Length: 331
Image 1 (cartoon, rainbow, N blue to C red):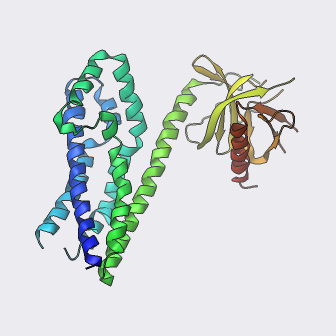
Image 2: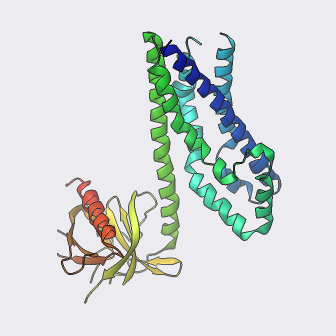
């Protein structure tokens, strides 16, 4: 004591809560994923995209849990080598690989499952009835899926305070690095989560695009414009005063697109004024007589007047564009 009390209560919390997690994932597998596989509610391809690696994800946490129990069983001085055995090196890259696949598809899964619940009464009853099983522990399917994420974020918290509570230098260094890996892991995961949300979103738009305006007319650089491999910085509804037009703007990492919304499709109507805009000369200004409107200019001028629904919106918009344009290196 006093360092030691926390060090054991926290090594205990790690074990206990890691087990609890492996039981959840197993409930998720047994009551939901496998049943819907046997019931062929979705084709298998798709179910594998709702739950991107449930089986192997179960195994990585179970293997971790197993290491901690064995180590506990044989005593808790020295735990660093254990931590390092699943968060660092080769096994670390695997844990990152598997965990991140599952997490990326969280948003997908949830909208995907909510849809089948609303469209198909047979599926809603199925879920209703599984969520009512004692083994669920008062959680809903919608509560379970996002736990793999929540877990990942508790790892540095837990490992951080096992470190700061270790009296012995060569062991503290082990736990410290281990916790470092957990931060590297969380950072990588968060990123490929946003890379998935973006990708799926941009893929949607890219097949919904209405390109025939550019294929026809300058501009022949995007004919043929592909946006699936671009970073979506921001998007939003917006009114676009073409003189004294309702539009959906996407601010990408280098282009600004002003898309017209005509049923499912998204038309880039070049209406003397272009609808595609390279940002590396962009610039914004307020409009004095309209606190909801701003100008955008590209240094043969070239003035795009875009009015928002509120002030704070358009304030935000100008900030984001000038930031992104600025983000871009001058050749």
